[PDB]
Structures are given as C-alpha cells and as structure tokens.
Length: 291
Ligand code: HEM
Image (tube, rainbow, N blue to C red; front, side, top):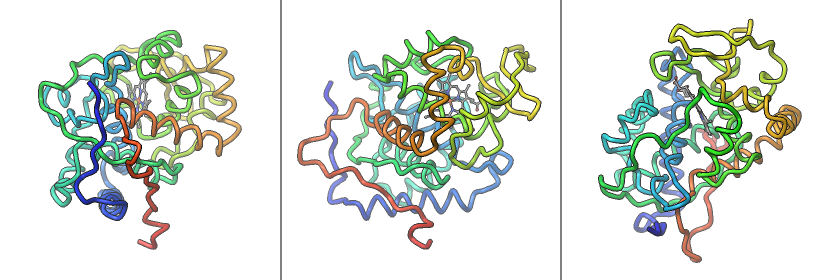
C-alpha cells in the first residue's frame, strides 16, 4: 500500500496558515483546560499517536489516513485522554471542512509546538482520509513500564534511530501524566506548556527516587514534584541514550533542530510525496503575524 499525498483541491499555503491560525487562536482562548496547562500538550500527543501507529514493514497505520476518527482507534486504551484534543479540533474541522483528518491532526501538533515557543516544524499537506477498515489495531503505541532495549526496538518500527528517539522524547517536557489515563501521575517539569529542553535537564539534574504511585506502578519522582516514566529514565540508564541526553541538555538550539526534523519525519512516515508536490510549509506563529 502506497499512500500518495494529494493536495486538497485548489489549496495553497495561505489556506493552511488560516487553519494554523484558527488552531492557534483557540489554543490561546481555551486556556483553562487541564488546570491551565491548555491544549498544547495533548495536541502534540494527538499528532504523535495518530502517526505512531505506523509500521515500516507494511505501511499500515501512520498519519495519512486520519483513522483516529474511527472508534477502534479513538478507544485504544493507549489513546485515553486524546479525545480532548479531538474535541478541540472539531470546531476547527467544521470551519475548514476541506482539510483531511490526517492533515488536521498532524497540523494540530505542529501548531501546538510552534505556539508553545518551540522550533518551526515544516509541514506538508496531502494526507487523504481512508476507510474504517484501514484503521490499525490497538497495541502499536508504546508501553511506559519498560527499559531502554524496549524503547530502542520499539522505535525501529517507526524507522527512528537513537538520536531521533531521544529528540522525540523531549516532548515530555510538555503537559503531564494523569493517573486515570495512563496509570502514571505528575508533570515532568515546571515549564509544561512552553517548549524547551527542560526534560533533559531534569533527567540529569533532579534527584530521582523510584516510587510507586497510587495505581501501584513504579515511576521516578523528585522532591520538586516532577516525575519520569521508566521509559524516560531508560534514556539515562543506557549509555548511548545518555550521551544524547547530555547533548540536548547542553544545547537548546540543537535540540530544537533535531526535534523539528524527527517530528516532521514522524508525521510524514508512510506518505509518498510526488516530485511536483508543494515544498513543505513553514507557518508563521500568531506572534510573528501580530495576531
Ligand atoms: C517510549 C515512548 C513513549 C512512551 C512510553 C510515552 C508515554 C506517555 C505516557 C504514559 C503519557 C501520559 C499520558 C497521560 O496520563 O495523560 C505521555 C504523555 C505525553 N507524551 Fe508520551 N510517550 C512516549 C513518547 C512520546 C513522543 C515520541 C511524544 C511526541 C513527540 C510524546 C508526547 C507526549 C505528550 C506531549 C504528553 C503529555 C500529554 C498531556 O499532557 O495530555 N510522547 N506519554
């Protein structure tokens, strides 16, 4: 199965900047969500989980088909809580009914990262909705209770290498774990709706204790009130990951650049872009537009 990007008919960069802007304005307006964290983090996670079902071996799952809109995928236990991101995007989709679902879920993530003062993420249009029977089964998203070997093997299926994995994991600066959702509780840091390299700094610099939470699962906790999942902590247990963690803790621009590449790649896995497709779009933030 080849998934060829097909530009929504007649649309160009300005159309998608209008969708960007509507997302960004609602992010600004709907600021109460999740104890004033706002929707940025869950939109980033929505983009990742709708992309992260991809299997490089047979091109099943991935962002192209926008299959999260079907009940098997929106009810995946791994996706618990993402319905909030979907509901956020609903009025956006109503205003811009021409955008595909995959394009909107992925664009939500791009828009969230950028509006949260993260790197620019080039974004390409052209995902096309595919039918209900193309929805991937549950179980393709990763478990959090595992070690570095698990993480490394997991991400090979998404064609991500060590650097790409460690960069992508930096998104755990954002938002928080919620006990009723994942069986883990707490934020990873203080700046959880501003995109920074804090995840790496906290991994290296906090004094972590291995504790059990109220769901009886182990997680790493600090006196500052932060947590790390076992899979996060694996990035400093594994010496290859550790080197990269230290690099990003010590170079914010490098983290931004590597995150941007890896996140675009994640969002584009499985998609074939024709030779004459438009170049990737780089959207202006609201701030850059004076909006
Ligand atoms: C080994 C890989 C990963 C595992 C096991 C993992 C696991 C988790 C878990 C358990 C949660 C908490 C869900 C909740 O209780 O609300 C979470 C939240 C989150 N994850 Fe991941 N994650 C991984 C990779 C990623 C990647 C690659 C990204 C995106 C680039 C990402 C972005 C997020 C964000 C932004 C949140 C916060 C969501 C919110 O506040 O609502 N994660 N992750």
